[PDB]
Each structure stands twice: as C-alpha cells, then as structure tokens.
Image 1 (cartoon, rainbow over the protein chains, first blue to last red):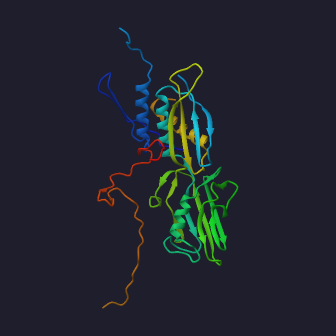
Image 2 (image 1 turned 60 degrees about the vertical axis):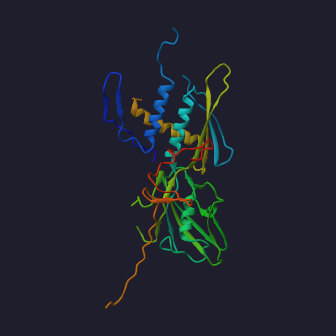
Image 3 (image 1 turned 135 degrees about the vertical axis):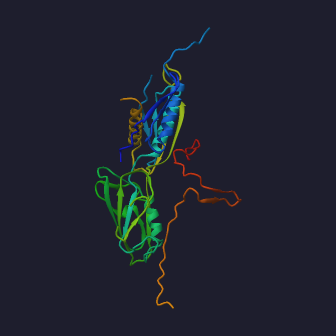
Length: 55
Length: 221
Length: 49
C-alpha cells in the first residue's frame, strides 16, 4: 500500500533552446496538479539566478 | 536555503492535531503547505473495513430480528468505524453481543495487533433481549477510496465500499515565525482532522516521503 | 396459457455517477460533470472542502 506508480517520462519535447516541453505519463490521480503547481511556484518565487536591479 | 523541521506536534484532541514547520523561506511555506495538504488528502495508509459477514442474514437489504436498524445501516455504520493495525496488512475482527443495549465498537473482540480507535462508536442497537449478533469484520490496509463494485464469493458475505482515508480535512495556515535575527521566514502550521488511525507526525512523514519519491522521478536522487 | 411465474427482485445500489441529473429545490438543474477528487476541491480557511 506504500507503493506508488512512479512516472516514467516518454519524451522531453524541445522547440527551442529557451523553450522546452516536458511530459510525464503515469504519475497518479491528483499528483499531476500537485507537482505542477509546486514546481511552478517554486521556480517563480525562488531560483538561484542573477539579474539587473539598479541602473 | 533553510530546511523546515518538525519542531512541534500539538494535539488539541485525539482526532484533531496540529503540526508545525518552523523554518521556511518566503514562498516555500505556502507551496509546501498546499502540496502536503493535497498529498495527505489524496492518499494515506488507511485501515477501513472492507467486507462484513453476518451470521444471520444473507444480503444487506434484508434485516435481522432484534436489531433496531437495517443491515444496510449496520454496514454503513461499520464503514464509519476505523481501526489501526500495527503489523498486519490484513486482519479479521469478530463482534459478539447479546442482550439489550447498543453494540459499541468497544464490544468488538480485538487482537493484540488491531485496536479500535474510538470505542464510543456504535454499530447497532440490540433492542430484543433474546437477540444476538455475530459479525466477522474484515479490515484491509489500503490507499484512497475504492468502490465496492470495482473490487471483484459466498452468498452470505457482504461487501461494503471502503474509504482508506484516515484524514478527513487538512487545513494549513501560513504565519510568519519570529527568528532572533532573520527575516522573510514563516512557520507552516497544518491542522489535521483524522479518525485517529494514523499518527499526525507519522502521516506527515509518509506524505513527505511520497512527495520526495515523486520528485526523484523529475531529477535523479 | 402459463404454468408458473417466477418473479425475482434485483436490488441495485446506484452510486452517484457523472452524467446523473442533480437538481436543487429552487429549480437549478444540472448533470454531474465530473467527480472531482477531494484534494482538488476548493477549501475555505477552516479547511472544509
């Protein structure tokens, strides 16, 4: 019962160097939204990167 | 970054418990709270009743003499009944009651491994004095909700849809912590309302392990 | 023209299913589009979905 269906991605689609599409087929009922929202908010709110702040 | 830890676990009651995650950066706390709530609600190890065998009646709709309510009502009450099993994924519970008076969950004969979380819970009422009910309760460890029709033998055996959802509601609120010299740090507090089968800290640990295992699909561990 | 008639009664428990018709008393009628999971449902600050 502790076991879960662990996703295995079939493809990582890339249109350009900057823009890529990643898909994971199996996942689990309700896990897809959780993972997507978590990743999206985590990489919007906090990512190690350097940008211009003062000019 | 800073890694949250289970600083405090508080139980306002047996059913309702609160867990606190003190160190969390801005944004991390709310993401973790939503993810943990969804993981806890979606799938947790549960031990709801699976099938009930009644000695006196063949199918759920027909009723037994001396019992206040229908056998279907008894089955649905047993669905609400929740137990926790320490070491066995499978267990059989036997219930025997004679004489007038309600048939509480405490009256269920229990092994050492299986313990009834709420003895006050009532299954049925034996109104007649010369009325005895004998029940074989089958409890299976499971995940999520499984309908009775989805599963699958003797005619006497009755199947009741199981709900392996130990947690009923999961509410998390994000409040800023007070670190001596720090800023933009908030503590995640999760309110767990559960039937009591699963330990709150243990449930949080299991949810975190499941989420980490799912994330290990995205990047190698 | 008949010898004996056998009547058998089937009891079917109908779980609420997508496509079933749901109607309030005020007249708002609609089908159940999807059985959304409990986690997906919106929840208030109290936590009840």
